[PDB]
């Protein structure tokens, strides 16, 4: 954060959906992009297709 004196700053953490793009202000990346922990941008959201189907997909398969 830009303080009164341009001398000592204060890096206040942004929200969970805000990426540290610049050093003075955060930005917002599009959907399916989770902000990374480090200053790298936004990583893609891991998407699956229910291959195993253990919790609530093996009983329908067995009945079928």
Image (cartoon, helix red, strand yellow):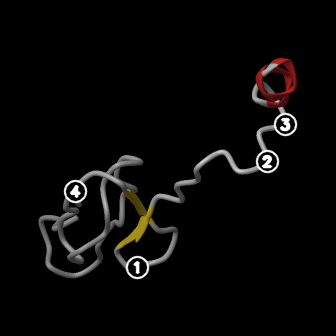
Q: Residue at the spot x=24%, y=77% of the render?
A: 23
- Circle 4 crowding by C-alpha within 10 Å: few under 14, some 14–19, many from 20: few
Report the side of 38 relative to 21 (left or right).
right
N-terminal of the pair, mark 4 or mark 3, is: 4
CA gap, disc 2 and disc 4? 29 Å
Instruction: Report helix, strand or loop for mark 4.
Output: loop
Quadrant for residue 20, please give it: bottom left
Q: Position of residue 7 (x, y in %)?
A: 22, 82
- Circle nearer the viewer, 3 or 1: 3
- Circle nearer the viewer, 4 or 3: 3
- Circle nearer the viewer, 1 or 4: 4
Q: How many marks?
A: 4
**Which residue in the protein does label 3 denote?**
54
**Quadrant where the C terminus lies?**
top right
Q: Position of residue 52 (x, y in %)?
A: 79, 47
Q: Residue at the spot x=52%, y=68% of the render?
A: 37
N-terminal of the pair, mark 2 or mark 4, is: 4
- Circle nearer the viewer, 2 or 1: 2
Q: Identify the disc placed on residue 30.
A: 4
Instruction: Report helix, strand or loop for mark 1.
Output: loop
Q: Identify the disc placed on residue 52.
A: 2
Q: Residue at the spot x=39%, y=81% of the render?
A: 40
Vertical comparison of 20 with 51: above or below: below
N-terminal of the pair, mark 1 or mark 4, is: 4
């Amino acid at each position: 954060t830009v303080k009164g004196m341009p001398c000592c700053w204060h890096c206040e953490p942004c929200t969970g959906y805000q990426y540290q793009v610049d050093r003075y202000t955060c930005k917002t990346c599009p959907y399916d992009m989770r902000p990374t922990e480090n200053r790298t941008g936004c990583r893609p959201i891991p998407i699956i297709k229910l291959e195993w189907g253990s919790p609530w997909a093996v009983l329908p398969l067995f009945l079928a």
